[PDB]
Image (spheres, grey):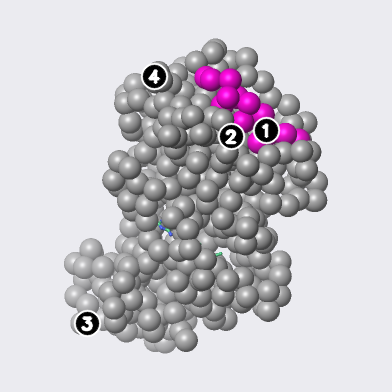
Amino acid sequence: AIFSDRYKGQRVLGKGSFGEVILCKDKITGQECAVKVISKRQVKQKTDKESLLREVQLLKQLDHPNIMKLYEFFEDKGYFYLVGEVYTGGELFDEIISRKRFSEVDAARIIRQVLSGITYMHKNKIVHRDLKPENLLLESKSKDANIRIIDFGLSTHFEASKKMKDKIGTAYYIAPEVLHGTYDEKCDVWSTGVILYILLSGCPPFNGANEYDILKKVEKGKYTFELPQWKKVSESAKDLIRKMLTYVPSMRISARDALDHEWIQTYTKDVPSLDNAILNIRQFQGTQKLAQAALLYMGSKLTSQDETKELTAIFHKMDKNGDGQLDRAELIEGYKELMRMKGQDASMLDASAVEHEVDQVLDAVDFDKNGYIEYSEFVTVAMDRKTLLSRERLERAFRMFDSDNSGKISSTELATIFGVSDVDSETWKSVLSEVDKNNDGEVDFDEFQQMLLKLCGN
Ligand SMILES: CC(C)COc1ccc2cc(-c3nn(CC4CCN(C)CC4)c4ncnc(N)c34)ccc2c1
């Protein structure tokens, strides 16, 4: 069975752990699904084929309201196609920051759902290991929507990326025992404890100016509740967090036992709003998403340098007599040749999607698609479109982060952003000196963009 014989791509949702995720549709039944596409060249398997196939077969039979439903699995020479149920509510934290109030009742209802999901998967001997806020999706845009946990089962069968653009926001949530090599299902309880701590305070329990500093704190395992906003929080919530953030996993509370904890029993069956927490989460989230967007922008610029020259070289080879003109079918053949090697665009997984993409570029530049075309102009527009989309994505993240609409990001804020982005301190300061030549101690959007261009060799 071939994935593209059955499914057509609608639109790219985004890059998640291990691969890009595409909204797809069954060509016969019209069923919509969310397909995670793992490139075999970029991601290495940890287990054999026997093991992976059996896991998939088990997962397809499992069913729980707080776990993503898996429908199908496909494999070809280059990729794995993981076909799951599509959820439309987005990431939990993105919904949380938009609401006016947030209490321990809201938090307890959220955590009960997470613990219920984890409990169920643990009964079936499946461990997540990489549990974090971006793995908590809302089933729909409804106010009361269930949480659906994504990526259960993946870490067991695939090695994680070492690229920082993939490792953003991982260090806060990882259990200490995962760092040293001996771990079991209890690591998921630790990660949920970290998430709970953040839900109630808006600040990570283990924090630092860069990834390795965060990991050092995690490894020591020590945290406190001495921040002012913990005065608002019930002792039972702090007691549960303690039990989930117990260092020795054998002494740490199980997921199933946490469901029976006083705090869950009291607050899920009077309570003020955690206003300081929601403000801190908004800053946390904003900071995290801008760091991610920065890395993705820089990644997109490098992909463009690579793809522009490769696409030009492919068409040069095709252009036999060398007059620079190729027809639409040839442009498709060359663009296929390109996306064939590169694992960048997952929405270009079959010939039909490539035909469509080529037509969109020709329609943008007002070139007639039924005659011969100046390929060098096609390349420029095809790449400039991606450059523009990348620029616009970054800008939206910049505006989101700039919550007072000042138009600026301060040096203190840059340190925070670049710290999360794990860009070396003297490196970004060096680039800031290049861009900020009046010692303003702040950058507008274009200046920020220029700093990022200088941080990826431009
Ligand atoms: C074979 C199993 C162990 C895992 O298989 C799957 C299959 C589909 C998946 C789909 C997603 C997924 N990922 N995403 C979107 C993320 C993609 C990146 N953006 C920036 C943030 C959200 C989804 N949105 C709606 N529904 C979904 N199911 C997803 C995540 C993990 C998945 C794992």
**The one of 280 and 396 positioned closer to us in this rendering:** 280
- For the magenta stretch, what is the residue range? 233-247
> Residue 222, image x and y in percent?
73, 26
Name above or below for residue 162 compared with residue 434: below
Residue 237: within the magenta?
yes
- From where the camera sits, is residue 446 visible? no
Answer whether labels 2 and 3 touch (C-beta < 8 Å). Answer: no
Dot placed on the residue nearer the N-terminal end, 2 or 4: 2
Q: For marks 4 and 3, give the CA distance.
A: 72 Å
Numbered disc in front, either 3 or 1:
1
Q: Residues within 10 Å of mark 1 (few under 14, many from 20)?
A: some
Q: Kindly indicate the quadrant of the structure image that contains residue 315.
A: bottom left
**Residue indicated by mark 1:** 243
**Residue indicated by mark 4:** 270
> Residue 186, image x and y in percent?
69, 46
User: Could you tell me the amino acid type at mark 4?
Assistant: Asp
**Residue indicated by mark 3:** 371
